[PDB]
Image (cartoon, rainbow, N blue to C red; front, side, top):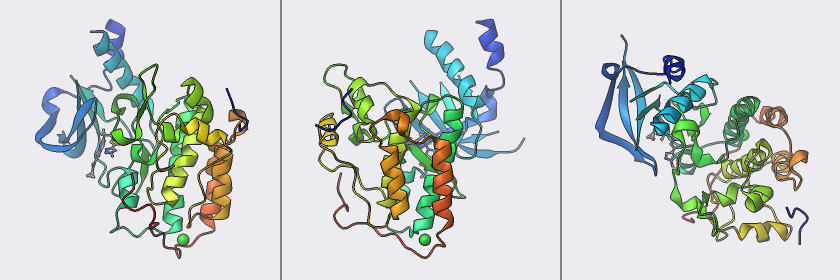
Length: 296
Ligand SMILES: Cn1cc(-c2ccc3nnc(C(F)(F)c4ccc5nc(NC(=O)C6CC6)cn5n4)n3c2)cn1
Ligand SMILES: [Cl-]
């Protein structure tokens, strides 16, 4: 690549994931939202009742649905969206009061500080550190794909059975293979090979940090296709946001290192961002840039 600028066992194994039919109520008349692979609705998981989000998806596929459930049920971490269970093709997930992280930071009625937004970034880094330690490559880390609960705990989401194209604006079709890919978040090497690694997740995380400090501006306005590769190979990176501290921009530039192996691990990012976070006291209000308002 160019990097210099120019089954009985499966049934028994899935038992701890399955929710019984009469112990879940799906409110099909209360839609939360629509995705490409399924519609998401409000639900009551049942003694004791707990509020949840239920995604309704569209034999080999049944085996894979159960298998994906088991794998997803093993991932338990405060900054990762947990699987509550499955029902058959329904995916039962915790309801996220504040929706996706991008919409949250863009909302003009919210008044985040620098500390708040760096805090969200730190939470995402902790989630990714956990997933990377399980050898799980996300492939689509972005602010739209993380969610926020009632305590403002950020959860890395959009993986496993919750995988979808949640905003179709930011997925571009590769002219040969036909794959719809999030090109504005992709590493230089993934743009060229369509292979993904933990180090390409690190690149994406850098872009996510940029999204946080801009309060959800779209990266690279009017560069929407795989021609982003050419743009990057001119010797370019996303500019430093007005409210991004110098040390955090230095971190973003490390995430976008041309050589994948020279990019920091998520362990390193958690360390570095935690230090930066600790220097702020909640005095710097972050406002939206006039030139990014209303732009796609
Ligand atoms: C732009 N955008 C991105 C997403 C997105 C991203 C990642 C993701 N991973 N899983 C899901 C889900 F769909 F399964 C799901 C799971 C729990 C949940 N809680 C709410 N609560 C709200 O919407 C409240 C504000 C009202 C919605 N979901 N959606 N994701 C949905 C939706 N839109
Ligand atoms: Cl602050």
